[PDB]
Each structure stands twice: as structure tokens, then as C-alpha cells.
Length: 50
Length: 49
Image (cartoon, rainbow over all chains, first blue to last red; front, side):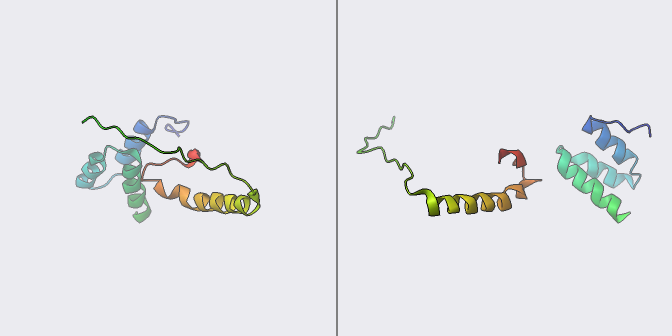
């Protein structure tokens, strides 16, 4: 409940990605993309897998 | 260079007899509505409809 009420998608995306705790290689693979939407494709595919 | 051209006539069509043409306007608006949202990751807007 500390991240709710959010407009900024950069802190949203990276907050989710660090709070999507994984092996750090794929943390970097999240960090690779400069695009937001392809990175969130990566993120939400991972979280659906979890 | 540089490049010039000359033209005979400037072709136009002002649409007359709009019934079947208007039905095809409805159909092509439907076709664009079915085509428009494919570029979610491929960077074209929904809101250009």
C-alpha cells in the first residue's frame, strides 16, 4: 500500500521489477530494454509464470 | 538535379451518388476498427481513429 496512488510509470516499472525478485541475470534482462511496454511484456510474462 | 515535372490535369473526385459508397464507408470504418489496435507494442495509437 506504499506504491498505490501512482502516476509515474518509471518508478512503477522499476519498483515492480525489483519487487519481482528473481535471479539477477533476468533482472538485468529487464534492465536492458529502454522501451516501457516491451519491458512490461517481459515483467508480466514473468509474473504470470510465477 | 534539381527535379521538376509538368502536369496535364490535377485529378479530383467529388463523390456523387453516395448510397453504396456510404455503405462502403460504413464497411471500411469497420475494417479500420478491426485493424487499428494491432500495434500495441508496434507503436501506433488507438486514438487516431
